[PDB]
Image: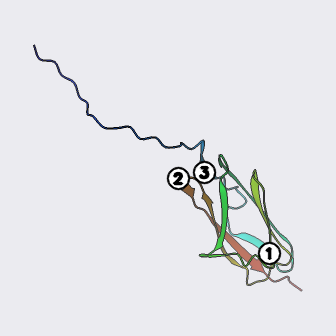
Amino acid sequence: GSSGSSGTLAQPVTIREIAEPPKIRLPRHLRQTYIRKVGEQLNLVVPFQGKPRPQVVWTKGGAPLDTSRVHVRTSDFDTVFFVRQAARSDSGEYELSVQIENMKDTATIRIRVVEKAG
């Protein structure tokens, strides 16, 4: 008779697979113009998920942090951002992207600095 079926011949593809995809868990306190005062110390904890070890990239508009005066303590678990004094200048947008074997993620953060009142 005549049966029906699909299929083709072609060597398989062997390639390592990812354990867990990158995910930038943004808190509710970051989903809004971060209002802060000048001089005060900044503290931002943006947790990230993924495996085996998701990289953490920090950029301000497109360029990486000067990493000269800023103290960025990234932990396998989550990353942490802090600053001695929040100068009105700092006020901008912090983009956080997670690098992975064959995956990548991005995120935006709004930061606003206001001069103390007197």
Question: Which quadrant is home to the C terminus?
Answer: bottom right
Q: How crowded is mark 2: few (under 14 residues within 10 Å), some or many (20 or more)?
A: few
Foreground residue, 73 or 38?
73
| Dot placed on the residue nearer the N-terminal end, 3 or 2 | 3
Residue most extreme to the right: 118
Q: In the rendered view, does 54 fall on the left or right side of 70?
A: left
- List x then y, in percent, for residue 44: 77, 63
SS at mark 2 in the image? loop
Q: For the residues carrying marks 3 and 2, which lies nearer the camera in this image?
A: 2
| Dot placed on the residue nearer the N-terminal end, 1 or 3 | 3
| Dot placed on the residue nearer the N-terminal end, 2 or 1 | 1
Q: Identify residue for label 3.
A: 22
Foreground residue, 50 or 41?
50
- List x then y, in percent, for residue 43: 81, 65
On residue 16, the disc is none
Foreground residue, 19 or 45?
19
Q: In the rendered view, does 44 fall on the left or right side of 94?
A: right
SS at mark 1 in the image? loop
The vertical placement of 71 against 89, above or below, is: above
- List x then y, in percent, for residue 34: 73, 69
Q: Identify residue for label 1.
A: 70
Residue in the picture at 65% in, 46% down: 52
Q: Identify residue for label 2.
A: 102
The vertical placement of 18 against 30, above or below, is: above
Residue most extreme to the bottom: 118
The image quadrant that residue 32 belongs to is bottom right
Residue most extreme to the front: 11
